[PDB]
Image (cartoon, rainbow, N blue to C red):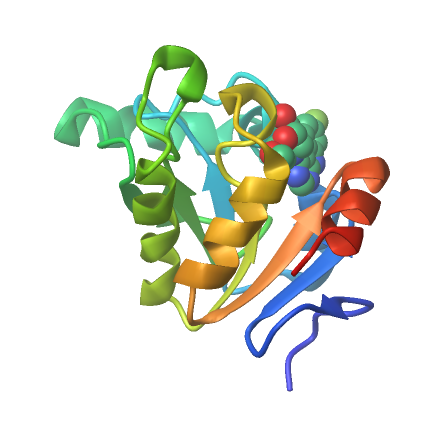
Amino acid sequence: VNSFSGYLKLTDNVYIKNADIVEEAKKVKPTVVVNAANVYLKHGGGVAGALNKATNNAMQVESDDYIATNGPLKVGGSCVLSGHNLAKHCLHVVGPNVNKGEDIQLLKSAYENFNQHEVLLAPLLSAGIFGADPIHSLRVCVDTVRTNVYLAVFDKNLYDKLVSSFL
Ligand SMILES: CO[C@@H]1CN(c2ncnc3[nH]c4cc(F)ccc4c23)C[C@@H](CO)O1
């Protein structure tokens, strides 16, 4: 048993809810929250900028030190940093940016990072401002992640569409 509430069970291990990941994280304080990041860990907008704003920019300060030491992430890669006031840990995961010409087949690689964590709160990767279709993103997730993933979908129209079109 875990503390995630009102989630709609989609498969053995994938759950979905119409919720803002920032508000979900603040309420649940999960072991792992996933950030949909970029290779530079530049959290200006979207999930990244919203989580970072919720940390009062502490996520960005920590991220800048990480990059100065280690250099950029790979598209499809990840790093574990602090969850600040939102979670124990933040798993920063880079899905492909299809508006940058980045291989959509790297989205599966992005979601493989989730398998290193038994339970995660996560958004849909590569959709929204990375240009890919949310319906496709949810499909890749279900077919790749084997650990227990709680998906917070911010847009109600999309959530209703993701559920209604789920095979
Ligand atoms: C489909 O992928 C992304 C997922 N994203 C979110 N998902 C879950 N919770 C979210 N809270 C937010 C607060 C914000 F200010 C901005 C975005 C979100 C958000 C919505 C959109 C962002 O571009 O697309």
